[PDB]
Image (cartoon, rainbow, N blue to C red; front, top):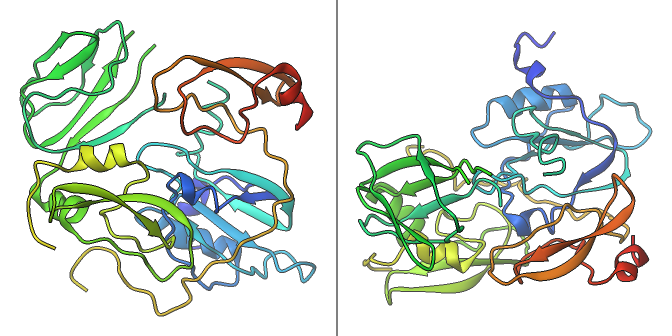
Length: 320
């Protein structure tokens, strides 16, 4: 039949919804291959074999049977340790996740794991998170996690590699990635890449020519490794970096059916889980949780949330 086990690791997902794309990539969903296999359960065995494939979508080509697959499609939906997929119901679309990932059955419904790519240094400081008690989990050498104020953890003993921690007061599996020079050229030195896709995405990228992060338009696909959804992630990856303007591993290569479409998605949204944001202030706002069908209040940072971010009791119930 399939001849290969693999198949079992993906749950057979429900119809109706399909991922929002215009927003899902606007959250960081790396788009990969778009294979042309005519069975859907053939298309998953093509997602096991992909380095960053976690979502296996298929159209159904309406009416003409079920397993005469119409699309395939391989998607990441992990902006570096984060479920950034966003779904919206319509019709004959059936999607395939991987149990792994599928932290959407976690995250249900409760500042997750961040993936900080930083330059090699020694006295590091970053987003505070008050109180303290930081717990190591990986380190070529031990790390001096010394803390002053106004809450601002400092991390000595850092050399190149990868370190995983735990913010025990309430914990957080958060990793620092002190990039190698092999990673500096790609994330920080490589010139940008608009890509062949016809897109409209907000991204940032570093210029080593003037020691600067600037802003550019992402076409959607095949983007180079110098590409950041937030300028904060841009600078953190770089600065302290100088420089001028099949043997690799993966990409670029597209000849040519790597060209995507924009589906219907009615309107109402709403129902996205709340996003506090990456900012500072304590702004009370109201969202609509659909497990209980009524609204609730929470503290907003001030930047980068979901469409479910009304302001009062009746503004939230008004539009859901």
